[PDB]
Length: 119
Length: 195
Image (cartoon, rainbow over all chains, first blue to last red; front, side):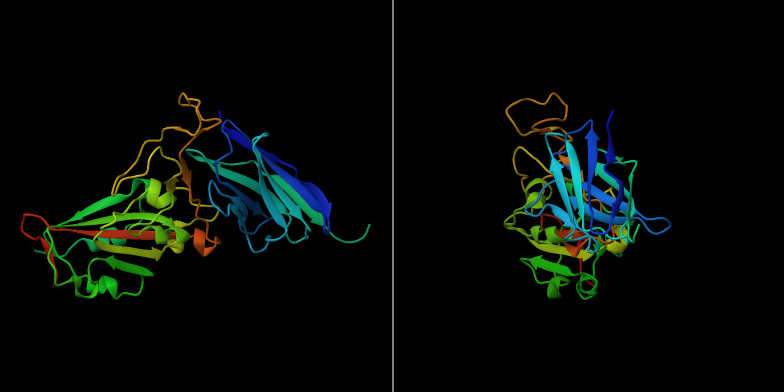
């Protein structure tokens, strides 16, 4: 009776923008730690961002995504957002959000593909 | 006498979570502390109220080894008179503590790709831990004036969270295996000594 499914993925171009939403159900995302992982076809599962249950500095990002990404915590909607800005075709993959509340709870994922070129 | 089981606590495959730290009672054996202090594989080997160098010359009635895993930024809280979520809600050292704190990086052992979620910690408590206390209850913490009825919600939160150690974390969020040695002197034959 506890789950979380993410949305907001899709197509975008160059220095675009995307709003992911990890919609959590069955528990209050208030003092919880959410992780963001991504998986590009074939390569290794990479850690993207993280927001911690406590801390003076509660935002955490990887070096590949720092400065461009922002992880938020909507308490009214009981969800966690991920603001991806100035995208690059190198960071397109499937994005997951994971939490721990008694046990590891996985998201199904979302597809983010950013493109480049002319059309 | 024989050798002390130091390799059992220092080289265990899986360490305990900080909220549920383990304790190993070591007795009836000769101990060589100089090899532990001079191995350089420990980034932190700080003794309080005793010299690490001439630690072998002393005999004690009992030696306690407390082992757990915290993160990099929390190692400085495993010290007397320190404050923080670890020292307040998870593992408190007394103000007049007498022993040694040992902590080394264990990212190559305690972190999985995609996150190792076995190591937990406590986030809330009604009142701070007394020295060497150990809380285990998973009761839903009541942060507000409304009761919780054993159900998580507003002002009611699960008091335990996981570190989720993954290899590419910053050093301040990587796993650190910590061993705290406590020496005990009692009206009883000193059972652990040096070589």
